Every structure is written in C-alpha cells, then in structure tokens.
Length: 98
Image 1 (cartoon, rainbow, N blue to C red):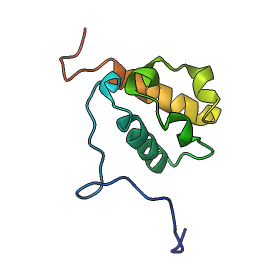
Image 2: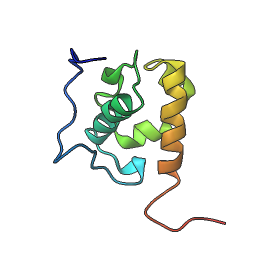
Image 3: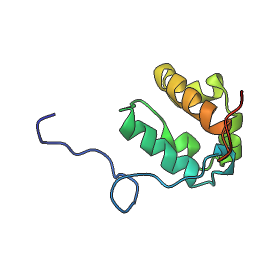
C-alpha cells in the first residue's frame, strides 16, 4: 500500500456502498455484476473472472455450485461467495427461523 493505489473502477453510489435486495435470486443481470465487484473490493478477492458473470442473472447465480464457480473464481474466493450467497439466499427481509 502506502499511496500509489490504482484499483479498478468501483461501482457507483452516494458515498461507498452497494444497493441490492436481500434475496440474491432477485438480482438482475446487473446486480450479479455489482455484488461481484463489491465482494472483491471488500474481501480483497483476486484471480476472479467477473466476465463469467457478465450476463449471469441472479437466478443463474444462486444455482451455480462450487464447481461452476471454480471455473470463474479461485477456490478461496469460491468459498467466500458461496458462503455469502448462502445467507442472502436464506433471507428475504423476513424473520429468523428457530
């Protein structure tokens, strides 16, 4: 670090955050892309092929598995994304089970 930082073009926003719905299945062809670049800049992910999800609708994003994800992102990242989407998938602005 220490200055000299020229990372990629972050997503658009008022200050610095993402605006997407709870359920990932409702994510549009754009949302899936926004959330991607986000988790990357947030969890400092690398070696990820965002292009693979250039046209992957939220629906096709929640159906993807470790394998399908491994063909676009590294194993490490595959564990983060899957884990993250795991919760968002089981959450629709509703109450908690148990």
